[PDB]
Length: 289
Length: 288
Image 1 (tube, helix red, strand yellow):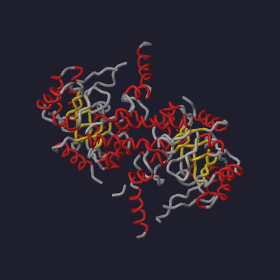
Image 2: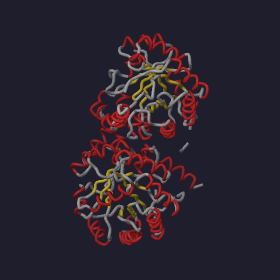
Image 3: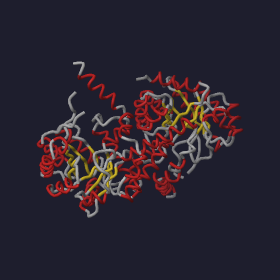
Image 4: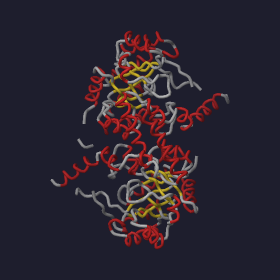
């Protein structure tokens, strides 16, 4: 709260990063603290996956979270860093109208971009089912209608369930509806990357998630195969939960945490990252005047 | 699963027990889950850990509603007794009443109130309220939220001395505090002398990089402590973890060399109890 950019300013800052020559590395941050470390690391864009946010709250990725829920966490990310944030919003949390509200809720939270997919949920009473191309298109039309200032990324899981060629047709159809970029989940080879890149006239997103169906290509490698941005969605929570495990086990069976001191953020680093000095100069600046 | 009153009396029995109660700080539900899986029987919600997780400084700028919110998230995920740091009650005697009720509704086992005087004037710094002022706040909680275990934190040692700290602590117990928190006692003889003249279960602050050495849980127990907290420890290890894997990704272009520092999918799978939700789904679909 010590001295920024508006939603469209953050949105236009996000587009230029995608339009830029170099590939846009987008790390996911489940909380505002992690968002700060990403900013301090040098990253220019932010990401919020439902998978990490749910796990952060101890819930499974089953769509049992509300759209407002995500908008609040996305707000903590923007407030703390003033960086362009890409938000995973599943299927828009409902029908065309729920998507519209979802879209507006994101703009209010000064979110630069959102990510909607073509999966069919809620699934009937553990499988990947898709909606009709028209159904997601309608959702895309709704977003552009109620929130034109919002950058759009469209996720398609058609490669797995339908096929490589049906995924491209869906992609180009999502593009003509208003989607600025395409998230093609589960492309299986370098050749599939390049062919998808050439057949679709839109920047491609890379899901660099761990222990998944994607080889650990470098960001430079994704850039040469036809991708203009790359995400590391659940990485933040992944290293965090592993760290809790270490320090908790230590305290539990040794009786102290004196062995994990090397794996900790010191007082000064917390102070600095949290910008205590800027809160002090504010209050003191008002004080001496 | 468990009611508030069941969780509160569970916290009480854990204190009355001879073995010292280790209470780690869990800034979020994920950290709370791992703490229970580690075998811990109680959780601590630090105001310093919470704020810094929300990218905010610990300057009393958060609401009691957003604290009870995160507190409830901790309780729901673990069904464990939770000790919540409510600072000063977030206002006058009236605000402490609502805060107490808010914590009860969030199924919180115990709360922690301070000697600190808030807000601080426009001019770092340290000052306290009057003894009568906090006693009134403790009295308010006992009246409004009797089902709530009360821990009173005093910071008189650093500003007013051990003498006033003891006199305040006993007045807090008289007000209804079930246990007390004596911040920053200077030595081991101050530990014993305080334990001697104060008639209540004592709490120990085992935070890092401070003026307190790293005793084991047993070493505190020998010195008379029944409970010891690890406030912002979970937040500290999470941050450095962010720093390492991000610097890796930014400088290398991949997270490949940090795969050994990550919780696997299957470990995350079993952590958030995905198996039980799936059992519930088909447990409904197959009964009809």
